[PDB]
Length: 83
Image 1 (cartoon, rainbow, N blue to C red):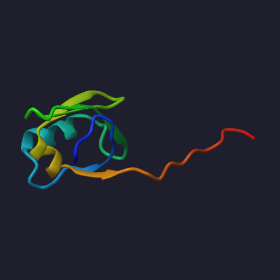
Image 2: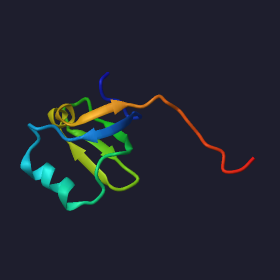
Image 3: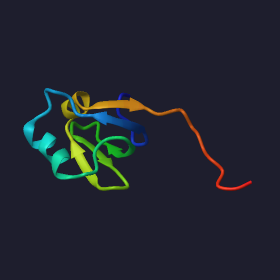
């Protein structure tokens, strides 16, 4: 139950073992870590991990997810604009 259809994963950064292709993609986009993303769905049949982010959609293999540094979020904090 490591991967679920609804999970808020925090993005900390890519691992060293990470491939040059994926790593380069981070360099190409100025949207580097520092936020969280939700999983669109998880295929137990044996398909890669499909994830969606308000920024863009992307799919990575299970191994790729393990390599990427991620952390679960449960802080649950909100600020009031006024009053």
